[PDB]
Length: 158
Image (cartoon, rainbow, N blue to C red; front, side, top):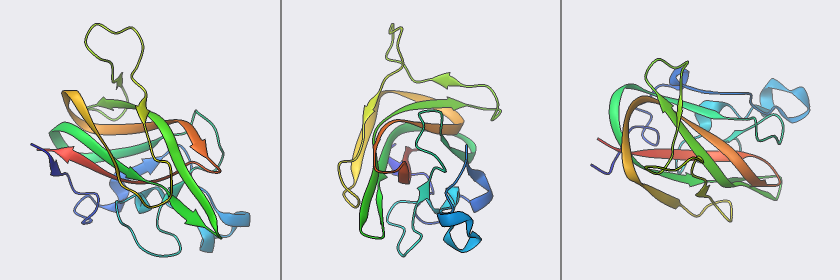
């Protein structure tokens, strides 16, 4: 139960990947870093999701399309005009209706777990949830970043 859930191979459609906001270089639609570009190993100039602002109130939401057992996550950052960008730490939340959420916590913990993220633009960083959760929706909540909040993702499970 550690299989890719569909982000990298486009099985999860673009409309199912949303975010608090997305970046547009100098407001040009042509320079959009759409939420649905946040797919592992996405190639090209605009190959990742980048939040409009660098705030801990930003989030990337993935609708798996159906309930799945989520056991892990893999992330990458990206590069924009020679500048390395990536999320260095993040929390995870999940749910089934897309409007109510549960922040991931170790059993008995009062604080949501903060997962160690990337440290560069292309290396894959995998985290395994010691306590898998069942859910249709998953959101990644950046807590720390380098230059910009930028992500490419893949969720693992079955």
